DNA sequence: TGCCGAGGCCGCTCAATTGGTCGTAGACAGCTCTAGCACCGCTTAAACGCACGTACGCGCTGTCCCCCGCGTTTTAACCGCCAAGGGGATTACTCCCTAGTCTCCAGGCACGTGTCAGATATATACATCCTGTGCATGTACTCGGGATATTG
DNA sequence: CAATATCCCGAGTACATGCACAGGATGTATATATCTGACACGTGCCTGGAGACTAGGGAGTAATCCCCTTGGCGGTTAAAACGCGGGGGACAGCGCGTACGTGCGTTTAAGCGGTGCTAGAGCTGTCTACGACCAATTGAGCGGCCTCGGCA
């Protein structure tokens, strides 16, 4: 399944940027849980703004507006 | 821009780029409050390491 | 010759806390956002730059969750992070319970 | 000055002794 | 309202005083998400002792 | 032993009264506004609407603070727990 | 005004604590919690006075403080708006 | 042996919850408002939505080509534990101060109206600023070789 | 002291950027406009002040051991480092959607007159809910009667 491609060393890199020294082996399968739910919650909104406008490709602006709605704004792709 | 005096010039590099603004907008602290609501794409994070993780 | 356990973990902090590059592989994350999407609307298409704005937002969320998690482990006398730490951080920020 | 706390404490004394009279007479029956 | 009078009934009263809102609006799983932002004035709190603080 | 402190929990989680004395809180809010402007007048319902929001913030913070004391295997809450609950919350 | 934050007397902080579900309160919680409450009052009554100054009123009114709360993610139901 | 000593089952008395009954006081539901001003119905001349090839932009697609993943195990101390000690958080009491009630009392000002102006909208003519395009170098980059720093 | 590593400096490196250019759409510019609401004027209210008093609470203390705090505990893995696998990475094209333009005609806004819905009225007029008090129940601990095990 495609979620297992968020590989163990990738979680370690993300964690290392965040500043943690030593990682329990239970954190790998638990962290995937929080990434999987976070993507679920912004893709619902991005596909909602898509279905509204009748087009059927998700644009960068759609994921920008979805992220903006939930208080997790990004400057980068179009404010 | 302006508070990038404290950054771009200090690294001896010309042309402001996204690893700056970050490494500034989240370092000066009258600001920060204006931009908390925003991540900077391609901006990374400021270095830290907490005082209990470094060797004693 | 071989370093002490601990030496290389602090070497990695000073590396990945100085770069700004993306940490998850492209294709494996691109497969994941397609699979989560097709459960809500069949036969989507994504613009090439939409999935990038997903990735740059995800990494910046994960990295923030760990930064707030380590604060818990440090408070609880440990240095190792464990699931019970994430469940605390994520409850005070009001996400899950 | 002192008369306020004195007459307050005097009022508390008659209050106490009224409660003494009542809660003593609760023993009648 | 359906679920709120649904709880005024259980406390055996007729008129829905303010706490009977809180004990639904911050008890039903979907309402707790819709009304996150709301403090119900004079609404009290949902009662709970933490399971680790009770003895034996 | 250790039971009367727990008997107070079951009391104050049933009542919905305001828990800070009214006049002492009202005189504090008059103090804090003077450094924003001299000679305000406060409408009697404004002072109440502050109190209702304060108590609801304080009691939310003690709910979120206790969770940290439990995390450290303690029972007693301490300032280092309030500090954690505010830092992780983003105050 | 003199020193009126001392009027959030120790027992009252214990009442708030007791509502929140805590058993034992170290003696340093009292002086910390006054610090948290004074910072919250400052950051809401400043907004409430700026809503007042816009309308040329002197009297602060319940809607001003409710609009002040509403913008900080701390909406209050009970006083209108 | 002994004795008895130590041993194991059953009515008072008190102390929270629990549920019941008393009586009385504003506050809720409802009426009539009445009153009026908004909703509606009825026209009008109105803007803006919308169902609909085609140029064609780019989303998706068939290939090869490699690091980072993937797998192992030593070890390394991290993290857990328990038990003891000290005090400081806690409890229960007595004295005390003010929180809170009510009551009187004024004028501050928030409330409200009474007029009608400087405000900004809208048009037409229009010039100009600004976009999209096309177009050199200059640097910030990736690499290789050596110096300095720091771990064990 | 040896070794792996980070730091540092110069060669050589595509294109990114800053610029110049054509030109188009819009910001300006003037005249006109009513009307927003500024401003001015009183209306009448509550925000405030100011007193007397109880009783609730608050503060204080005293005694103390619970809980925290600490040391020392014994047990097992994340880290270290390597070997080792496959998988993320870099090109060829199809045509489907998206855009965009055309002419698609649905509905709204506005101004019209009529009229009934609602929201401020009451002491409405009570009487749910609010104290106030009584009564039941369970549970716990303390006396008291009675077999048996270890000792003379």
Image (cartoon, coloured by chain):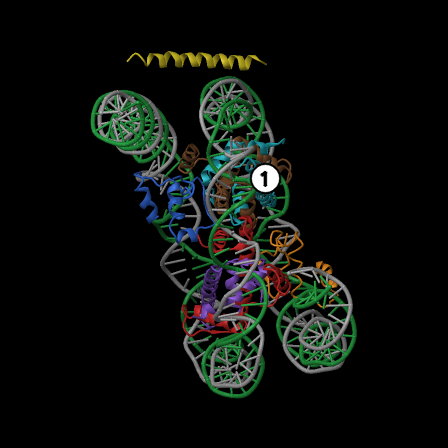
Chain colours: A purple, B orange, C red, D yellow, E blue, F brown, G cyan, I green
Kindly identify the residue that appears in the image at 35 percent across and 48 percent down.
E1
Residue closer to the observer: F48 or E23: E23
Drawn side of residue A19 relative to residue B2, left or right: left
Instruction: Let me know if residue F64 appears in the view.
Output: yes
Is A51 positioned to the left or the right of F86 in the image? left
Q: Is residue D1 above or below residue I127?
A: above
Quadrant in which residue C15 is drawn: bottom right
Q: Where is residue C41 drawn, in percent x and y?
A: 41, 70
Question: Height in image: I40 above or below C92?
Answer: above
At 39% from the left and 14% from the top, the residue drawn is: D19
Residue assigned mark 1: G35
Residue D7 picture location, percent across and down: 51, 12
What chain does mark 1 sit on? G
Res B13 quadrant in image: bottom right
Residue F30 rendering spot, x and y as whole percentages: 59, 35
Q: For mark 1, give the secondary structure.
A: helix
How many labels were placed on the picture? 1
The x and y percentages for residue C48 are: 53, 74
Along the line of sight, the residue nearer the viewer: A13 or C55: A13
Between G70 and F66, the one nearer to me in the picture:
F66
Residue under the point 57% across and 45% down: F83
């Amino acid at each position: 399944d495609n979620i297992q491609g968020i590989t163990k060393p990738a979680i370690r890199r993300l964690a290392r940027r965040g500043g943690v020294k030593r990682i329990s082996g239970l954190i790998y399968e638990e962290t995937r849980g929080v990434l999987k739910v976070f993507l679920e919650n912004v893709i619902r909104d991005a596909v909602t703004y898509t279905e509204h406008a009748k087009r059927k490709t998700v644009t960068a602006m759609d994921v920008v507006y979805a992220l903006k709605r939930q208080g997790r704004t990004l400057y980068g792709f179009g404010g | 821009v302006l508070e990038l005096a404290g950054n771009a010039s200090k690294d001896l590099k010309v042309k402001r780029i996204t690893p700056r603004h970050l490494q500034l907008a989240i370092r000066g602290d009258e600001e920060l409050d204006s931009l908390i609501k925003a991540t900077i794409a391609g901006g990374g994070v400021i270095p830290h390491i907490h005082k209990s993780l470094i060797g004693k | 010759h071989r370093y002490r356990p601990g030496t290389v973990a602090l070497r990695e902090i000073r590396r990945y806390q100085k770069s700004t590059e993306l940490l998850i592989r492209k294709l494996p994350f691109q497969r994941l956002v397609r699979e989560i999407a097709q459960d809500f609307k069949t036969d989507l298409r994504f613009q090439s730059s939409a999935v990038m704005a997903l990735q740059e937002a995800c990494e910046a969320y994960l990295v923030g969750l760990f930064e707030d998690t380590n604060l818990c482990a440090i408070h609880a006398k440990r240095v190792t992070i464990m699931p019970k730490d994430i469940q605390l951080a994520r409850r005070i920020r009001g996400e899950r319970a | 000055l002192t008369e306020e706390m004195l007459l307050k404490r005097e009022e508390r004394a008659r209050k106490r002794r009224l409660q003494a009279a009542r809660r003593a007479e609760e023993h009648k029956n | 309202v359906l679920e709120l009078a649904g709880n005024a009934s259980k406390d055996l009263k007729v008129k829905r005083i303010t706490p009977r809102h809180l004990q639904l609006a911050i008890r039903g799983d979907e309402e707790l998400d819709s009304l996150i932002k709301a403090t119900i004035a004079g609404g009290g709190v949902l009662p709970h002792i933490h399971k680790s603080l009770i003895g034996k």
